[PDB]
Image 1 (cartoon, one colour):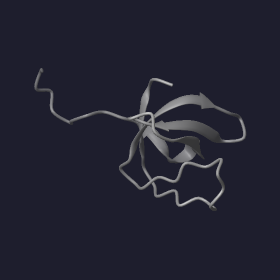
Image 2: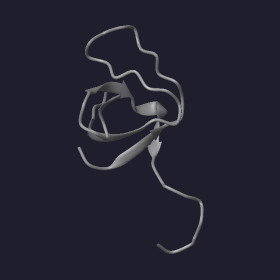
Image 3: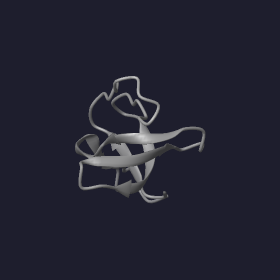
Length: 69
C-alpha cells in the first residue's frame, strides 16, 4: 500500500467480498490503481482490504493549517 486517500463519497458497495465498503471521510491506504477504475484499498490498521472506486478517492491531507508540527 502506503499512500493515504480519503473517501469523497460513500461507497456502500454491492455486498461483494472483493469490495471494501467506505463512508465519506474514511481514510485508507491504496496499493493499486487499475484501468477499470478500481483501486485496492486497505484500512489503516491493516484489518481489511478490498477494491473501491478510484473516482471516490482523493489524496489525504491531515489539516488545512500551515501550522508546522
